[PDB]
Image (spheres, coloured by chain):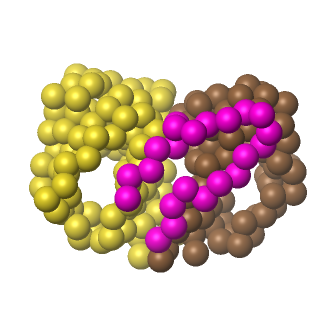
Chain colours: A brown, B yellow
């Protein structure tokens, strides 16, 4: 029932892992090596994206927004977006079911 | 629209601040000085609690769980709990509005 987003971290590839799931949400960790891109990403429900460590750029619509450690964005359901890592980064993606 | 949990942090008092809210959630930052206690905390919706910086002990039921940086727990609505800060800590409390 406690999950540790900063244990088991790896930057040898882009890693996407569901760390926990309940009836309402999935809690997903993304480990992004510096320079990794996640393009055309779309989740089936509303999400929030938070940088636990590192720094990304996040694109949605015609916007491009830097997200240093601690930054959070929330999106409505099914909105297409892109993540680019500027450093090795650990992201929490919280997905509504 | 982008909120920055680690800007504007202060440890002179226990601080609870809604940094953003949308249709489904309020995103709340708790800044806890070392030694601060939030006891008998109960939220009206399902929550998740995650340590962004620091370290706390989280109690629920008869359990006492250590939460270092990065640890996350999720609770159903209305479940009573306690947070104790073992260091100056910044916590994200994500509160469902359902």
* Residue B79 x, y percent position in the rendering: 23, 67
* Residue B47, quarter of the rendered image: bottom left
Asked if B48 appears above or below A30 in the picture, the reply is: below
Q: Is residue A86 left or right of residue B20?
A: right
Quarter of the image containing the C terminus of chain A? bottom right
- Give the camera-side residue of B68 and A87: B68
Does A2 lie within the magenta span?
Answer: yes
Asked if B34 appears above or below A27 in the picture, the reply is: above
At 64% from the left and 28% from the top, the residue drawn is: A54
* Residue A21 x, y percent position in the rendering: 51, 67
Asked if B39 appears above or below B23 in the picture, the reply is: above
At 15% from the left and 39% from the top, the residue drawn is: B37
Image mark count: 0
* Residue A24 x, y percent position in the rendering: 49, 74
* Residue B91 x, y percent position in the rendering: 37, 40
**Can you see residue A57?**
no
- Give the camera-side residue of A15 and B46: A15
Q: Is residue A22 left or right of residue A92?
A: left
At 56% from the left and 65% from the top, the residue drawn is: A26
At 28% from the left and 41% from the top, the residue drawn is: B66
Quarter of the image containing the N terminus of chain A? bottom left
**Can you see residue A62?**
yes
Does B29 lie within the magenta span?
Answer: no
Q: Which segment is the magenta one?
A: A1-22
């Amino acid at each position: 029932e406690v999950v540790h987003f900063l244990e088991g971290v790896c930057f040898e590839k882009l890693h996407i892992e569901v760390l926990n799931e309940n009836s309402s949400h999935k809690e997903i960790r993304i480990c992004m090596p510096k320079g990794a891109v996640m393009d055309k990403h779309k989740a089936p429900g509303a999400i929030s994206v938070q940088v636990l460590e590192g720094k990304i750029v996040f694109e949605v619509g015609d916007e491009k927004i830097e997200m240093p450690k601690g930054a959070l964005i929330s999106l409505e359901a099914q909105v297409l977006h892109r993540l680019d890592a500027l450093e090795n980064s650990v992201i929490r993606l919280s997905l509504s079911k």
